[PDB]
Amino acid sequence: DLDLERSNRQVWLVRLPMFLAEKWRLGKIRINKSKITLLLNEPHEYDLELTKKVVENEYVFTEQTIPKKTAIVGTVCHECQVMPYHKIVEQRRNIVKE
Amino acid sequence: DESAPITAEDSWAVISAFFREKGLVSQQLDSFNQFVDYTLQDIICEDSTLILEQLAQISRKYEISFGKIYVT
Amino acid sequence: FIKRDRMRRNFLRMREYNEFPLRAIPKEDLENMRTHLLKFQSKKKINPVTDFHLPVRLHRKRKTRQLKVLDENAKKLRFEEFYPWVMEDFYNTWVGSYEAGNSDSYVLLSVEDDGSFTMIPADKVYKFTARNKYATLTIDEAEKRMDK
Amino acid sequence: TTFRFCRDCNNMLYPREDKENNRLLFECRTCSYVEEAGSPLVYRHELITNIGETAGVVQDIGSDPTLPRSDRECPKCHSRENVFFQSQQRRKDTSMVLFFVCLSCSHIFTSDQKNK
Amino acid sequence: SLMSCISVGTDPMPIITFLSEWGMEPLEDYVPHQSPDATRVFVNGVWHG
Amino acid sequence: DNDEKLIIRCRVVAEEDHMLKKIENTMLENITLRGVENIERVVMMK
Amino acid sequence: KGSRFISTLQVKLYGREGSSARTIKATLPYIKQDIPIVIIFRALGIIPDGEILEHICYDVNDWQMLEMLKPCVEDGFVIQDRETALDFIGRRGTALGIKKEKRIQYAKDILQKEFLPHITQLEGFESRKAFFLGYMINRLLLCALDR
Ligand SMILES: [Zn+2]
Ligand SMILES: [Zn+2]
């Protein structure tokens, strides 16, 4: 009984620098009108690049022969990677068995 | 002065400071040392786990693992 | 002309904008559902599933004492899931495949009615073939023809 | 030679003679898609091949330390700072004619005084 | 030769990791026609992007 | 020979192309224009 | 590190220069006969020929390479589907499977594991191996063009 809820929803995909993404495994976005950034809770601000302006054929879904519980989320609207006290993070990046 | 360019004869001083560090037959010693520190631990770790499957009529397992290796 | 060793004597005698907040959803929703990207190989740019028509479905298609060989939990689970899914109307058919390298870092930003967003971590990523377009399945017969 | 691909089949188009209109088309044997030809040309072998001589020119070529430098001025921007190298096609009969690459306009200009 | 030495080798993982963070595009996103001039990147004969 | 561009054109009396492109090879390789086979690079020497 | 692998891949360009229908077939581990490259790509899961050309040749402008591709494209036209390709590869070699249901999975398993033991043996990286293969094909042709 698969059902498309909307697909109308637009989502953006983020490639996030790895340590923060792993930690996630809240902020506030300021959009500058074609340059945009994130004001974090404390901390850094970040710029996010418009990575791919046109993203089509790419949609997001969820789950709940074996058919299973199925629903659609929405469309990938735009592709984005995050860009980045930034001195400390750069130094940690530089630092990067028995 | 300290920042001046260097003459050719100077270069020998470098080479001395090289062999003081390395020694003539060093690659043998360093390669072997790396093998002793890392390879033994990795070889043992890679395939250590072995399990025996025991059947009864209830089925059963036996298992032996290999840990940190010790050298004398 | 000769080699100078008197360097012991020499060295001794010398020395508008808009600010929209972000939030992590209550994990209960996350607990209910895993989220997976969708990608098509079509080259047909549009491909909205609305265009795909309907009805939509999306579904996946005596020994003595002896030895067992060992394996990992994550790999074993992924391997045990080899029935790939698929979708159709009652016909257009897409067949997906685990990207497997891109799990990596993918953070979802859902645009909601208000400019604020919710963000969910991406589970996996899949790549959907558009399959059986010209609809000739020539199979064993095709291989036999090849044997020409 | 510069053959196209089908739509949604993406496969290469094989030329089809139209006997009805006596004109050339392109068929995709996996589907019904056929479109018109843009040229009577179909196949070109080009036995003797002069292309690939200038191959490998890169935006960063001026940064290559292993390449020699020359003082000859460019015909366009008249910049005497340039890097030169021989024909990239590797074959027995390949001529030794140099290709000078300016470091200003990136232009490629040869050293050959016979044919230009 | 006197000053020649033989490499004892290291682990590729930290390097491979380090690349992506500096903007290496992962192989799977590569579209040859669309990004023609990009230099492709090998590590120990394995091509990561 | 007067033509600054040397041109040669040919035609013939069910998938015709492979047959033609086939004939192209016979033209290049399988036609000995003149001279004795197997011989190459005949050098005049005084 | 480990197992001291001898496994070797070869990519062979058939036919002598000047003779048309020079084609490209590739050997695999445990398979008796060489398998054409388009077939290998179909097994990897890339059906459409245009995509395969894109993987092999990275410059749309060069006609020459694309030209020498067409024989391989023709064989690919003969075998048009992924599953059909996997069945074909499995049938071509290692007859101990004896059962079609297991043999196709077995061919896929070989591609994931034994084919190109570097890169990865993990599942889902087929896309990753695909390009590296095309890269080889590129380099080989790029030799046959005397570049
Ligand atoms: Zn088509
Ligand atoms: Zn110039």
Image (cartoon, coloured by chain):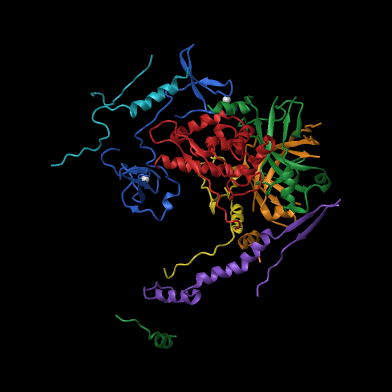
Chain colours: A orange, B purple, C green, D blue, E yellow, F cyan, G red
Give residue G20's quadrant in the image. Answer: top left
Percent position (x, y) of residue G66? 47, 34
Q: Please give the name of the residue rendered at 55% of the width and 23% of the height, measured from the top-left corner.
A: D29
Q: Is residue C48 visible?
A: yes
Residue at x-position 39% and y-position 49%: D103
Of G65 and G58, the residue lying toward us? G65
Classify C115 as above or below A97. above
Residue C57, percent from left and from top: 76, 30
Picture quadrant of ligand 1: top right
Q: Nearer the viewer, residue D96 or C62?
A: C62
As drawn, the residue found furthest toward the left would be: F46
Q: Quadrant of the N terminus of chain B?
A: bottom left
Going by the image, does A43 lie left or right of F12? Answer: right
Q: Nearer the viewer, residue C110 or F18?
A: F18
Residue C109 found in image quarter: top right
Extreme residue in the right direction: B57
Q: How many numbered marks have been drawn onto this rendered protein structure?
A: 0
Q: Residue D33: where, in percent of width, then height?
A: 57, 21
Looking at the image, residue D44 sits to the left or right of residue E9; the answer is left
Above/below status of E43 relative to B20: above
